[PDB]
Length: 168
Length: 164
Image (cartoon, rainbow over all chains, first blue to last red; front, side, top):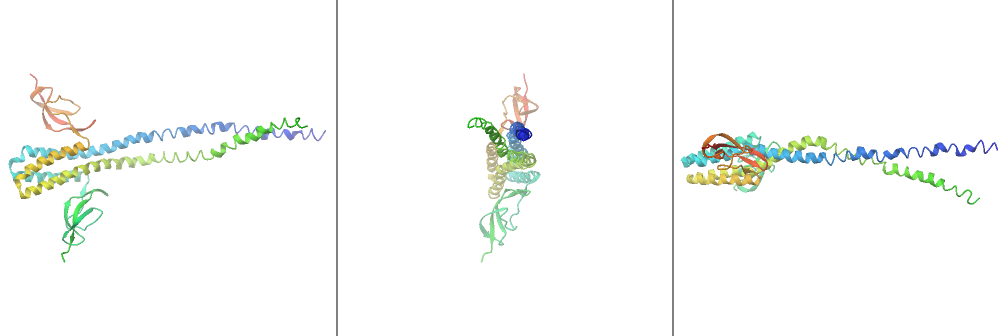
């Protein structure tokens, strides 16, 4: 009577504890789909942008090769200029080649490439490839069989070298 | 009694399931902001990595080239030595070094642009004047021009043939 009719809400107050658990699970529809946008739009660019730079990179390198090739072609030119003219005198060509070499250096310096230390300097593994040793001051480069270069911190290529050794 | 109340127990089967479609969502969807947080930490990673990547990437090319061309400098020294003993041989060395240079260039994939006798082409040639030879054709190459496949390392300064 006044105990089942007044407490009949036993299934009434539940309407707010049920429709709500069915009012939120409905909104989560764009919670696994709506988010599928910010995601599938971020993973659509990460597989795109990285594909765009996959280009801008292989290009910046190509650009680097060119930058060098261009700076160095003048040597080929001088080699040509020598074969067609310089043949004047053996000591004329000798001086010409000397000149070409000197040029190659300036060109390298131009791209900021310095030659690592050599004959007389301290043998240093960071810049030197020791091929064996020859008479000279120990711990010091006795002879350079191949110039080594470094541009800044980077090693273009180490110098193949002979390290000094005191005779007895 | 047995079915007058059990046939209702079917309604409770829904509410019992409602806690499976929303209780399982926030289960795996509890990290859908994480497996995404990383996908943005890597996509926001390149955004700053490229400025560097690209730079050092050019150095890569320059080194790649220098690496391949230093042998020329090596041969120049080698040549100067053969000449220190027999001056006459110097001419022979230069010829070798020069031919060497071409091979190297080939190695990096650069070819010489069409020359003497070949049709003038602005893609590769820089006409600076005229000189005897088939009209509209390269008559003499004053400076070699090279192309790396599509790109142009540098154009050949050339003289084009005069018609008539």
